[PDB]
Amino acid sequence: PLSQETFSDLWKLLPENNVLSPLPSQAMDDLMLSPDDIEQWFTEDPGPD
Amino acid sequence: PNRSISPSALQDLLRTLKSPSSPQQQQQVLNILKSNPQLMAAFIKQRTAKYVANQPGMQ
Image (cartoon, rainbow over all chains, first blue to last red; front, side, top):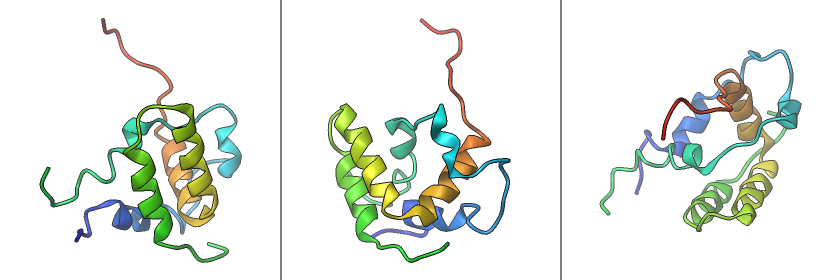
């Protein structure tokens, strides 16, 4: 019903095995996400409208 | 990486995403993500390195 191009496979590509940033998940002290980025990872779905 | 996750949270994110614009939608996304630290911590760590808090000269 979906593909390896959708959000469910994009989770696997994240840096869950590395350390990039100089600080942990507590970084949200002055930043919070928007729905425009949430509607990006599901758009790859090979279905109609 | 300290514990497991469930695919049900991904479906709950999709049902939440389709709702109209409201502060309750933001709270539900945070509620859903906090249940599965594994993927949300990797996501924020990847995002903070590319985060953009403003917009260009438009009208």
